[PDB]
Image (cartoon, coloured by chain):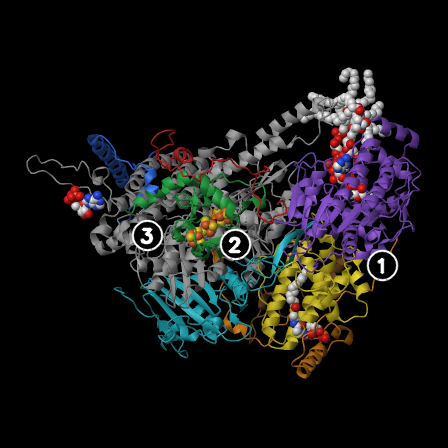
Chain colours: B yellow, D orange, E blue, F brown, G green, I cyan, J purple, K red
């Protein structure tokens, strides 16, 4: 059966895509600085193999770090759609999560999840650099496990069908 | 003329010519110009409702001349025909035709020109800007409409239709 | 010779149109002297309270 | 003309061109320019010209008619367009095969 | 206006180019040395110790 | 007029061309209403440019 | 002084320190705290619903500053990443659980903070 | 060198093909998702040969109705909006807001003034902002490691922020006519002194690779040059203004000083060339001088001398007294001068005094009442003159609160100073203007 | 107020047909003076300021507007005196204020202009002060002031294809519409607004 | 029981519609649209799924149907456990089923399982739960026991079992639905782009087709929920007009500007190859079998007019989805601006 | 140990001895982040509940 080959290759693919996890160079608000702080030496991102890429075509993670305004929501949707699959989305900050300090505003979208599917949320205002690091590492672990979460059932011979 | 609408703001027809070897011309009325709009001076003050009405008619004329290009670039031609969009914007203007303040009319014309320029330059999204072109009481041409409400409430007053429809969630 | 074509009418333009009162469109490129840039000596003017 | 205006006239001075061509601000309009009776674009007066040419003159009859209308209707009710669903008059989108 | 005073970048250490900044460095090091001397002479450091009985 | 060739000055102002030459509406508009356009007026020149294009 | 994850404390006897005075709700700049209170059968002034919208709240600390009985405390926890937006709608259950889990460190910090004025 | 004016400029003549745009210009959307753009700038750029010609900036991508929300909320609950306005001068934004509130109240924050916090932490925040600005400018120009070197010091300063207020960013520390004296600690001052001593090393590391580099000099010198008149016409202020030699500093102004600055002997720097190189040098010198200001401020609260024995002529150090551990005592001047106020503050709280409890309850339910009136209070933030114009109607909420941000005025001149420049020069100009769009919008 | 201060009476000496209404308060800086200026003279006054000798070194620091129609004294109503500036807020539709700084005189000068016409017409000064362009654009969009003879009337800090004046007291902070994503249209759309009330 | 459903359709996503719906098999092409139809009026939507890969956009975008606190995703669903179905539909008064055999599956056993076992278990769970007011099962047009297609053969039995278990079940029989993420227009575009010279047909292309827009299908679902009398009846949904496969190719070619080219492979050899080789989305036996079969609306059951939905014509509906893929021939200079 | 690692204080938990941390009767054992797990925070009235 293909599973004999698929499962080890699945593990290798998950390991490779976890090791190389390039987010998009996109910051909107104060949460950008926290992202830069994680990128810089005190909490090196590179240790976990995450390197930022400017073009969405070369990005695996969409770091929605900052407030999203109605004047920008179409742009965020276009960026998400133009990012090559497979991809994940991480909301950072109260403003990106649920509107934050500007939830009662006439210009701010009440949450980036309304425009985009958000894979993970990192609470904070601003989230600490270690908080962002924790969120990214948790996202990486979940990403590695997503390939095979025990969906297929095992038959009498222990081979998934 | 040093303006976005100037006759010299046309897009050249060729790398080495403007549309001909014996003449110079270009299209800037039905499409966007060559150089971007760096400044849009305020409409000169109108002292009369006559001048205000003339400004409204000229703005509507420009909008009608530009609508086919807007539809083609935004891929919203299927939703409504060019004439349908013109008539819908005409209804939009008709709702505001009661104005009798030249200053307010000038401000409105400035805003209209700005939004028209945004539509030309793709600053706005098609779904966000089609709210002005959408029919007031007619279905969109790219969708199948539901006449269940009309069948159920045929020859019934709008009050009764609204009464049956409701105006508040019933769960709470 | 190719450049001269754009120079032909500049004289009449500047003669008949005010360069400051009239809003005339033009394009230009800013030049820097690389030798002066490399030989420049950094310095600032320090300001303190009166003594 | 350039030297009269004050443009750079030497190679070493070419590096301060922007200070003499673009940086200098333009004199603001005289306040008398805001009091003109009319601001319509200038066009040649086609009096004494043929009727065919006069056809291209600005339509003063439209201005007279508009003035009459606005004198007759200083105040009007705000038009309301019914939003009630109506079957489309142009049924081609839902009744076309090809 | 008539007797300008300029700061000139002429060495690797920009502090050295200014007499004031050299004195700032020296004062900082002097303060650190004084603190270290006082603490060493004292020989220990009192500290706040959490006590669970504080929450009776 | 000094430095303007055949251009000569009238009572209420100085002309923009030689005596017998024809006045230019576009030049008049540029001078009087420089940088300001209430609307894109379609003159004969603009219409002919559109037709040529 | 670090402000991390909100939590609700209790007295050493186990009684809730939160009395529904709504000072924290009013001081919350982002309107992230919702409080509804009804008398308890024994007669105590205790809340029946105490919700903090972690997505709408700016971790300013105004809630713990305005709390007159140190009921709501922004404890040091910051690794509170959530995969679902609903998981960030902290309820009274979640806040009390956070307080029960993090009481030791929170109490240790509060000791020093209270002793500083002395 | 011969003339090149005709090769350098191309005017447009009426209805002339040669004197016209004979090319289809490149209309690019610089940003918002652009590494050079800060993230919320949609600049429509008209490039012709990769040389900027026409600018149409759109800056509404970060508009959030901050002023509307401040009007809706009472005074205290609107302060964190000022932290959000600028991501690197939040302390200065808070200081301006509190200064306006206390000007309306008719009082001054004597506690903060005597504790020196509002000057030392303002200067630390100035170091933060200048570090970030210079690092981003170097990153845009091409230099890479400067961002890491500057952000290490930024992390240290953020640690100081968190230690004083518990938030490494968006401190929300300054408040009108109140100070958290408990947070202020002597060991914090000693750590700040150590940071100041080590900051010279980072300054020199950046200075060695940037200041004298031929490429850096050729990139910045004679780019963005402007006169005082431009500085005056476009309301340029702070570093942008001082680069013209205007010699305009609000901290050293007789009628406009707002903290201990007017009674400290520090120096402000200006350049005779209004270019990016002079602005970069000014930022470096201001970072260096913030160390001197912080040192003076900390010395103002230090007990250097000590009792000397008559017999031995040597210091008599207290073995079991806190003052032996440290030479800096933050509460020294406050206790010495305002003894009654200090005693009341440290003895009466809301757990034992009815009046304190009532004040606390009112303060946290409806903010302090502010008498009706109009005020305009400004500070010399790292990016220029940052001001608040507040109109109060006598209630617990501000009727109007307008924010004068230097970033907006600095971004207004970007077309003027960067018209004839290349794209590589424009990306340097955006960094030299030192703009963050939080306060622009 | 232990500084040397002089009133900016030059404006009213030159514009001999205007009456002077000036204020100074300790709520402001020692060198800050407020004055009332009529709208029909605002443009000429700015022309004089921009090129007078001692006012030549003047920069327009700030500009904004206040919706004085809904202004009410919430506390100490009886303490109001006829000399207070608040008396001009009542019953006036709008109040646009400009603030300049002069370097020669080391002074700050604020000018208040009352707009009583319903359309809020006032002459722009962005042709005199360059930085006033975006300031007036923001003021016009947020409060609906119809600036005349303005270099650029296009919106700045407002969303595309939307007309509104949020800073007016009538407007609600929650707005009137919210932007979501429509699957049927496969793009961001804007629809009516439903929000949360604390 | 009672089939009445009181819900308010005048509100946006943040309103309370009054519908609590569980939508099985929402990871397909039509699943997100059907879910969004209910979600956009404020209804609560549950999406039970066991989909690989979990991180697929198909699973991810289901969260956008309703919003936060209204849309829920139930992962690792077990399709042979009754307790799982009970939990899924415990609080739902509407149960929509779109779990059908995929076009990629040729195994008769798997097709029958998907189209019968899951549907019957869902119907039984609905019968057990007395709060399930409405059940809407999605069958296929042309379902028949004699149908060569295993999908249709099993779908007929599936709808019979659903009716037997839950007599108040509403069965839809849509024709070939088209849309942005469909299997018809997108497949046409992708096949023509991958070959660049032809579309591979395996028949005379005389089979009749009656395409319907997915928006129209969603509107039909909403109208069926509104209409109480629609319960317990079978509906066939299709476009206003019927076209053959050749006519559909001609219409698409004319709309997009791409010249048509149909390359014929013998039906027998194509069937043998597809039934003896691995099958995926773009190479499957179901497509070959359904090429010959007619999938149109018959008069044996209720039609869309009964639901009171006016479907849009195929030429008008499909034009917007081919704007990007347009032949670039001789065009005006003004059109060059784009 | 979270505070000890973060350097908030120099005291650390000590099992079976004089501790610097209070041990109340209602305390619960520490739990790691339970998001993306069936034992995750479910708001009352949420569809999952
Ligand atoms: C070296 C040792 C020394 C001795 C020599 C040994 C031999 C040396 C050989 C040297 C040359 C090798 C060339 C191949 C290199 C590797 C790649 C490869 O194998 O092809 C896969 C590769 C996959 O396509 P892709 O472009 O990578 O996919 C991009 C995306 O995935 C697509 O993205 P999308 O979104 O557009 O998706 C659209 C959809 C596809 O688009 C659609 O939706 C429409 C199409 C759906 C149905 C597709 C059915 C299969 C069509 C096959 C077409 C073959 C091309 C020629 C057709 C001619 C028609 C007249 O996606 C797909 O399904 C992708 C295509 C899947 C193909 C599956 C089968 C591939 C393997 C078998 C191919 C056998 C072809 C035999 C041809 C005749 C040979 C004489 O390309 C092909 O499929 C074409 C391969 C054609 C050459 C086959 C050579 C091996 C067999 C030769 C005959 C036997 C040996 C004879 C010599 C013996 C000597 C002793
Ligand atoms: C470096 C590693 C290279 C690995 C390359 C693997 C090539 C394909 C190997 C196929 C082995 C088949 C074993 C016997 C199968 C028995 C089941 C059966 O019914 O046979 C007919 C099978 C079954 O397909 P079916 O559709 O006819 O029936 C389905 C099965 N039943 C009916 C039981 C439900 O089909 C085949 O023709 C063979 C399997 C084709 C599988 C195609 C997908 C391969 C995926 C490879 C993933 C790894 C990629 C590595 C490279 C990654 C690079 C980053
Ligand atoms: N052209 C069309 O779209 C038409 C569709 N229909 C009917 O409408 C339904 C919805 O349309 P569409 O989105 O196109 O269909 P899809 O094939 O895209 O979706 C089928 C759904 O059922 C799931 N599924 C498939 N097999 C099984 C299985 N053995 N066990 C459990 N779940 C399974 C699939 O999940 P998974 O991803 O894990 O495989 C998927 O979610 C169709 O299933 C079909 O019955 C009728 C006529 C035309
Ligand atoms: C591309 C998308 C663009 C969308 C633009 C949206 C923004 C539009 C801005 C607002 C435009 C207006 O309402 S401008 C409002 C203009 N004001 C008036 O029209 C009042 C005076 N009216 C008249 O003179 C006549 O009624 C008249 C109807 C003109 C002719 O009618 P006929 O003689 O009978
Ligand atoms: N621990 C201390 N904390 C704050 N201020 C102190 C402290 N010790 C001395 N001061 C200041 O020192 C001055 C008295 O000097 P000195 O007699 O040398 O100190 P001490 O008697 O405490 O040893 C006072 O201003 C007093 O406020
Ligand atoms: S969540 Fe806080 S820190 Fe992040 S962008 Fe919003 S206001 Fe700034
Ligand atoms: S941290 Fe601030 S915003 Fe968040 S709940 Fe507490 S008081 Fe409200
Ligand atoms: S947490 Fe504190 S402030 Fe909030 S209601 Fe309870 S007792 Fe009052």
Residue at far front of view: G42
Separation of residues labelled 2 and 1 (CA atoms): 47 Å
Q: Label 1 crowding class (10 Å Cα cut-off): few <14, some 14-19, many 20+?
A: few
Image position, residue B162 (x, y; %): 72, 67
Label 2 is found on which chain of the structure?
A
Q: Is A156 in front, or is H138?
A: A156
Q: Is mark 2 within 8 Å of ligand 6?
A: yes
Q: Write the residue at 9% across / 36% down.
A: H313
Q: In this view, does G36 lie to the left or right of K18?
A: right
What is the distance, in whole Å, between disc 3 and disc 2 at their CAs? 27 Å
Q: Is residue E41 visible?
A: yes
**Residue bearing the label numbered 1:** D92
Dot 2 and dot 1 residues touching (CB under 8 Å): no
Foreground pick, H64 / H259: H64
Residue I124 position, x and y percent, is 51, 67
Query: Residue A136 location, x and y as percent?
Result: 54, 36
């Amino acid at each position: 059966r293909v599973d004999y080959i698929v499962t080890p290759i699945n593990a290798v693919v998950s390991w490779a895509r976890q090791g190389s996890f390039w987010p998009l160079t996109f910051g909107l608000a104060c949460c950008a600085v926290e992202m830069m702080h994680a990128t810089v030496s005190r909490y090196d991102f590179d240790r976990f193999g995450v390197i930022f890429r400017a073009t969405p075509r070369q990005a695996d993670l969409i770091l929605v770090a900052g407030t999203l305004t109605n004047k920008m929501a179409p742009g965020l949707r276009r960026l998400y759609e133009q990012t090559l699959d497979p991809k994940w989305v991480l909301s950072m900050g109260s403003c990106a999560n649920g509107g934050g300090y500007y939830h009662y505003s006439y210009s701010v979208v009440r949450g980036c999840n309304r425009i985009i599917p958000v894979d993970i949320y990192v609470p904070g205002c601003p989230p600490t650099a270690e908080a962002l690091m924790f969120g990214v590492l948790q996202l990486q672990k979940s990403l590695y496990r997503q390939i095979n979460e025990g969906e297929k059932k095992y038959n009498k011979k222990d081979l998934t069908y | 003329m040093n303006h976005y609408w100037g006759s010299s703001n046309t897009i050249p027809a060729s790398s080495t010519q403007n549309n001909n070897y014996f003449s110079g011309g270009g299209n800037n009325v039905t499409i966007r110009g060559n150089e971007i709009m760096e400044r849009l001076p305020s409409q000169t003050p109108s002292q009369n409702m006559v001048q205000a009405s003339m400004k409204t008619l000229r703005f509507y004329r420009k909008f009608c001349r530009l609508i086919p290009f807007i539809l083609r670039i935004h891929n919203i031609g299927t939703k409504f025909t060019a004439q349908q969009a013109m008539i819908n914007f005409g209804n939009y203007i008709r709702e505001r035709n009661h104005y009798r303040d030249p200053g307010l009319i000038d401000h409105r014309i400035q805003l209209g020109y700005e939004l028209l320029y945004e539509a030309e330059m793709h600053f706005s999204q098609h779904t966000i800007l089609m709210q002005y072109l959408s029919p007031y009481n007619t279905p969109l041409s790219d969708r199948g409409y539901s006449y269940l409400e009309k069948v159920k409430y045929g020859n019934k007053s709008k009050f009764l239709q609204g009464f049956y429809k409701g105006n508040k969630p019933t769960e709470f | 010779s190719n450049k001269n074509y754009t120079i032909v009418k500049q004289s009449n333009l500047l003669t008949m149109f005010d360069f400051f009162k009239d809003f005339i469109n033009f394009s230009f490129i800013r030049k820097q002297d690389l030798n002066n840039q490399t030989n420049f000596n950094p310095s600032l003017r320090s300001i303190k309270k009166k003594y | 003309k350039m030297r009269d205006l004050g443009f750079p006239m030497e190679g070493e001075e070419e590096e301060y061109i922007e200070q003499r061509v673009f940086m200098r601000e333009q004199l603001p309009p005289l306040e008398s320019e805001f009091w003109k009776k009319n601001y319509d674009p200038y066009e040649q007066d086609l009096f004494h010209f043929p009727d065919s040419f006069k056809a291209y003159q600005q339509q003063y009859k439209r201005y007279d008619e508009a003035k009459k209308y606005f004198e007759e209707n200083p105040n009007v009710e705000a038009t309301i367009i019914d939003r009630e669903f109506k079957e489309p008059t142009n049924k081609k989108p839902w009744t076309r095969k090809y | 206006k008539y007797n300008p005073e300029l700061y000139i970048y002429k060495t690797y250490d920009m502090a050295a180019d200014d007499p004031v900044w050299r004195q700032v460095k020296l004062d900082l090091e002097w303060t650190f040395e004084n603190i270290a001397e006082r603490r060493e002479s004292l020989g220990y450091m009192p500290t706040f110790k959490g006590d669970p009985n504080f929450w009776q | 007029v000094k430095g303007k060739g055949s251009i000569r000055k009238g009572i209420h102002g100085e002309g923009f061309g030689a005596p017998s030459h024809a006045h230019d509406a576009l030049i008049h508009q540029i001078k009087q209403s420089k940088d300001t356009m209430d609307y894109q007026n379609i003159t004969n020149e603009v219409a002919q440019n559109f037709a040529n294009h | 002084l670090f402000r991390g994850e909100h939590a609700l404390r209790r007295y050493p006897t186990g009684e809730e320190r939160c009395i529904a005075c709504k000072l924290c709700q009013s001081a919350c700049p982002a309107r992230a705290i919702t409080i509804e209170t009804e008398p308890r059968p024994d007669g105590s002034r205790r809340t029946v619903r105490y919700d903090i919208d972690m997505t709408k709240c700016i971790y300013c600390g105004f809630c713990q500053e305005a709390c007159p009985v140190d009921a709501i405390v922004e404890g040091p926890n910051y690794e509170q990443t959530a995969y679902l937006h609903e998981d960030l709608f902290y309820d009274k259950y979640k806040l009390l659980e956070n307080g029960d889990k993090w009481e030791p460190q929170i109490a240790r910090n509060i000791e020093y903070l209270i002793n500083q004025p002395l | 060198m011969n003339r090149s004016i005709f090769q350098l400029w191309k005017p447009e003549s009426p209805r002339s093909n040669v004197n016209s745009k004979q090319i289809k210009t490149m209309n690019v959307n610089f940003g918002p998702q652009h590494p050079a753009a800060h993230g919320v700038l949609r600049l429509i750029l008209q490039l012709n040969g990769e040389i900027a010609e026409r600018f149409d900036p759109h800056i509404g991508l970060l508009h959030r109705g901050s002023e509307k929300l401040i009007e809706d909320r009472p005074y205290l609950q609107g302060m964190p909006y000022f932290d959000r306005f600028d991501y690197v001068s939040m302390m200065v934004q808070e200081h301006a807001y509190c200064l306006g509130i206390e000007s309306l109240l008719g009082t001054t924050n004597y506690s903060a003034t005597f504790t020196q916090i509002r000057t030392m932490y303002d200067e630390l925040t100035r170091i933060l902002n200048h570090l970030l600005a210079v690092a981003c400018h170097a990153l845009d120009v091409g230099s890479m490691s400067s961002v890491f070197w500057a952000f290490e010091e930024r992390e240290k300063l953020m640690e100081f922020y968190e230690r004083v207020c518990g938030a490494r960013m968006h401190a929300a520390f300054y408040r009108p006519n109140e100070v958290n004296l408990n947070a202020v600690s002597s060991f914090l001052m000693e750590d700040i002194l150590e940071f100041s001593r080590n900051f010279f090393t980072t300054l020199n590391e950046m200075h060695n690779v940037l200041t004298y580099n031929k490429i850096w000099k050729q990139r910045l010198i004679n780019i963005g040059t402007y006169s005082f008149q431009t500085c005056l016409d476009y309301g340029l202020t702070g570093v942008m203004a001082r680069s013209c030699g205007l010699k305009r500093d609000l901290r050293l102004s007789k009628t406009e000083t707002y903290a201990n600055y007017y009674y400290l002997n520090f120096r402000s720097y200006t350049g005779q060339h209004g270019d990016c190189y002079d602005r970069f040098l000014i930022r470096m010198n201001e970072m260096c001088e913030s160390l001197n200001i912080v040192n003076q401020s900390i010395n103002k609260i230090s007990k250097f001398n000590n009792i000397v024995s008559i017999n031995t002529k040597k210091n008599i150090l207290n073995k079991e007294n806190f003052n032996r551990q440290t030479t800096v005592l933050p509460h020294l001047v406050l206790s010495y001068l305002n003894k009654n106020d200090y005693n009341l503050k440290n003895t009466k709280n809301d757990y034992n005094s009815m009046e304190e409890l009532i004040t606390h309850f009112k303060y946290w339910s409806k903010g302090l009442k502010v008498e009706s009136g109009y005020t305009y209070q400004s500070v010399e933030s790292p990016k220029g003159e940052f001001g608040v114009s507040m109109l109060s109607d006598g209630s617990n909420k501000p009727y109007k609160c307008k924010v004068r941000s230097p970033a907006l005025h600095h971004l207004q001149v970007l077309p003027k100073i960067g018209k004839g420049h290349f794209l590589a020069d424009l990306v340097a100009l955006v960094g030299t203007v030192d703009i963050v769009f939080g306060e622009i919008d | 107020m232990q500084n040397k201060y002089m009133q900016p009476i030059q404006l009213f000496i030159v514009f001999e047909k205007l009456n002077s209404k000036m204020w100074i308060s300790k709520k402001l800086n020692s060198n800050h003076s407020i004055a009332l200026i009529p709208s029909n003279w605002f443009y000429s006054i700015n022309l004089f300021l921009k090129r007078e000798l001692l006012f030549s070194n003047i920069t327009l620091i700030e500009n904004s507007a206040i919706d004085t129609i809904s202004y009410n004294l919430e506390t100490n109503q009886n303490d109001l005196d006829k000399t207070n500036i608040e008396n001009y807020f009542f019953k006036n539709k709008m109040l646009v204020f400009y603030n300049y700084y002069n370097y020669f005189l080391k002074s700050k000068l604020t000018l208040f202009i009352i707009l009583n016409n319903l359309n809020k017409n006032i002459d722009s000064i962005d042709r005199i002060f360059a930085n006033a362009n975006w300031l007036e654009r923001e003021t016009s969009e947020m409060y609906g002031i119809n600036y005349k003879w303005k270099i650029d009337t296009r919106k700045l800090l407002l969303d595309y294809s939307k007309i509104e004046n949020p800073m007016l007291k009538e407007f609600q902070s929650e707005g009137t519409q919210d932007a979501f994503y429509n699957i049927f249209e496969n793009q961001v759309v804007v629809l009516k607004n439903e929000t949360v009330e604390l | 029981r009672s089939t009445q459903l009181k819900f308010y359709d005048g509100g946006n996503r943040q309103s309370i519609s009054g519908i609590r719906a569980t939508i099985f098999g929402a990871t397909g092409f039509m699943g997100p649209y059907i879910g969004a139809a209910l979600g956009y009026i404020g209804s609560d939507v549950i999406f039970p799924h066991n989909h690989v890969y979990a991180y697929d956009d198909y699973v991810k975008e289901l969260k956008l149907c309703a919003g936060s606190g209204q849309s829920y995703i139930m992962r690792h669903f077990n399709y042979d456990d009754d307790n799982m179905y009970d939990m899924a539909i415990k609080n739902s008064n509407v149960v929509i089923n779109l779990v059908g055999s995929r076009l990629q599956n040729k195994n008769f056993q798997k097709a029958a399982y998907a189209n019968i076992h899951v549907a019957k278990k869902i119907a039984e769970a609905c019968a057990r739960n007395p709060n399930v007011r409405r059940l809407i099962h999605f069958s296929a047009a042309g379902a028949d026991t004699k149908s060569p297609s295993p999908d249709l053969h099993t779908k007929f039995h599936g709808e019979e079992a659903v009716l037997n278990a839950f007599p108040n079940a509403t069965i839809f029989r849509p024709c070939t639905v088209y849309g942005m993420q469909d299997y018809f227009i997108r497949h046409w575009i992708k096949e023509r782009d991958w070959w660049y010279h032809f579309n591979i047909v395996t028949d005379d292309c005389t089979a009749k087709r009656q395409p319907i827009l997915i928006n129209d299908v969603a509107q039909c679902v909403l109208n069926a929920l509104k209409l109480q009398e629609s319960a317990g009846q079978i509906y066939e949904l299709g476009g206003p007009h019927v076209y053959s496969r050749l006519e559909v190719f001609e219409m698409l070619a004319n709309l997009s500007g791409r010249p048509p080219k149909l390359a014929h492979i013998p039906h027998d050899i194509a069937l043998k190859i597809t039934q003896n080789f691995y099958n995926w989305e773009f190479f499957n036996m179901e497509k070959v079998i359904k090429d010959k079969l007619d999938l149109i609306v018959t008069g044996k059951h209720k039609t869309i007019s009964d639901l009171y939905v006016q479907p849009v014509s195929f030429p008008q509906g499909a034009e917007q989805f081919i704007d990007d893929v347009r032949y670039r021939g001789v065009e005006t200079h003004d059109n060059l601006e784009k | 140990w979270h505070g000890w690692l973060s350097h908030q204080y120099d005291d650390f938990p000590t099992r079976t001895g004089n501790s610097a941390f209070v041990k109340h009767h209602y305390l619960k054992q520490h739990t790691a982040n339970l998001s993306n797990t069936p034992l995750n925070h479910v708001p009352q009235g949420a569809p999952q509940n």
